[PDB]
Length: 186
Ligand SMILES: NC(=O)C1=CN([C@@H]2O[C@H](COP(=O)(O)OP(=O)(O)OC[C@H]3O[C@@H](n4cnc5c(N)ncnc54)[C@H](OP(=O)(O)O)[C@@H]3O)[C@@H](O)[C@H]2O)C=CC1
Ligand SMILES: CN(Cc1coc2nc(N)nc(N)c12)c1ccc(C(=O)N[C@@H](CCC(=O)O)C(=O)O)cc1
Image 1: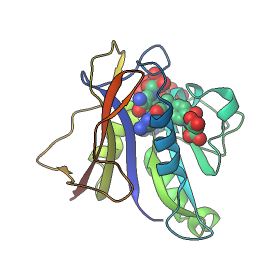
Image 2: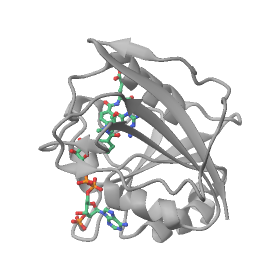
Image 3: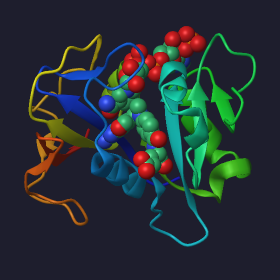
Image 4: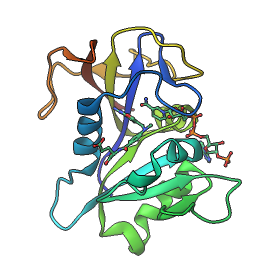
């Protein structure tokens, strides 16, 4: 209905995951920021939809599943029904966005958030239209097995600031990271 956005936390070597989990120790305010951005709707009586791939879903502790206050959609071609806790299942990202325009959800969803994995990001990314990427830069290297695709600076502009997103360097468990927002329209 509203805006299509991606949200990712990536290490300096572009890593987003390792053996089913994050490559760094848990960062509690990085998690807090993920939840405040995905859960806040810009219009009353609306909710945000969060789209993820099957291993992203299973990477979330079972006790926080489904993500609360959000419409949880799982992307999968192998699954027959949404996994336990999930609200929706689609076989592709267009089917997922085609569903948004179904009276079902059409008067219900403000913003649409893509939360992972790389294949989903790679795809939302080349998709046409207005897109924003919310990138948390974890400023160090971490052994990964899964990476974020390359941001094309000829298409995405790094914004100088964005309301509700801290512009300075954060630090936790001794890891420094900073929050960035990029925008596209093509
Ligand atoms: N740090 C961060 O910001 C993030 C970290 N992570 C971490 O990264 C990893 C998850 O990674 P990734 O491996 O990339 O996993 P995904 O979560 O993207 O899983 C891939 C599965 O999802 C389904 N799928 C994905 N894209 C599509 C599509 N376009 N159409 C239909 N089905 C699709 C397929 O399921 P099937 O095989 O069933 O068809 C595919 O096997 C974990 O390590 C997780 O903890 C994850 C996201 C964000
Ligand atoms: C592997 N993922 C992806 C993920 C982790 O961190 C991120 N950070 C950003 N910026 N982007 C992402 N896409 C993620 C996730 C794992 C677990 C939860 C999770 O438990 N979320 C609770 C967190 C609540 C809390 O931590 O207190 C929630 O309500 O969102 C979310 C995402």
